[PDB]
Image (cartoon, rainbow over all chains, first blue to last red; front, side, top):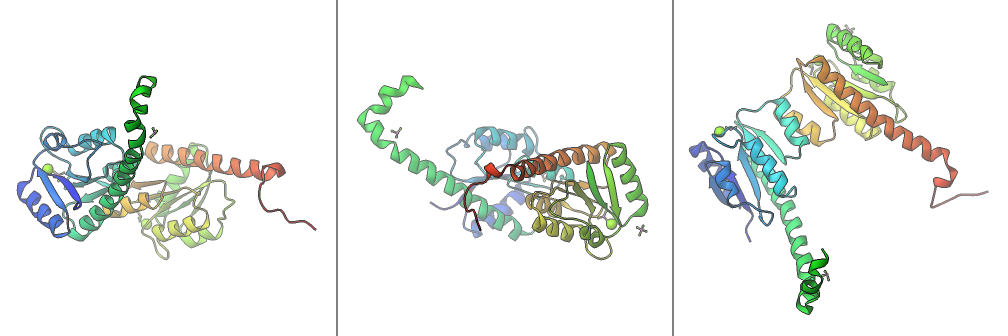
Length: 151
Length: 143
Ligand code: BF4
Ligand code: BEF
Ligand code: BEF
Ligand code: BEF
Ligand SMILES: [Mg+2]
Ligand SMILES: [Mg+2]
């Protein structure tokens, strides 16, 4: 499976330039004009990472970040904005954002950061998959189903 | 409540020192990062608050020296010449805080008191274990 990304920015042209950059870097990139749209495809099972702009109509990037945090704190999120400042960046990192990048930005900073974030996301997902695979026995023995009500 | 405060801006350094003293800290202030560093140790019970752009060694270089000295000695960076990538990296590298000038007094003070409490808890645990011969496991050496 190729590394994947959900990319969000209301600036359509920059969105496409960023998608083009990331696919050059090896990612499979789904893009969206808004955070709410992207959320329709996000869940704790998401194999990739989220790269999102901040200032958008409706739900802004910081609000999306909180929703991702609540959905799965192990799902990496990188914020990119032309409207941030020192204090916002510090707070976002402390809140757990994977990276906080200012526009205009070097494509290599974005790429290297996405690359590492996705590798990290993959390690988490492969371990979750192994854990589930190891549960196959109990489920097939019907042990899981019979013990179900004990949770 | 102890603090080493470093800034080449004399008026600001004096004002930060009064503000920190008002908050209850005993402050040792310096214009030079290396003079400040020379009076530090891994036994220092306080925190370090340093400016970034300065003659001689800069605050980021001083921070890297403190990390190697004792990664549990909190460093708060304050600067009027920072940007987003520099602040992000400082926090990711372990800086306790990164504050842009101009800052509100209460922002500097709250960050200092929390950092100091964090350091105080670290030193107490270190003190308590050395006091207790019985807390030691592993290799012993005997005559
Ligand atoms: F002028 Be000073 F900063 F050396 F005190
Ligand atoms: F609108 Be984004 F924050 F650049
Ligand atoms: F896979 Be264990 F038996 F829950
Ligand atoms: F000169 Be300091 F970095 F404000
Ligand atoms: Mg925008
Ligand atoms: Mg200075």
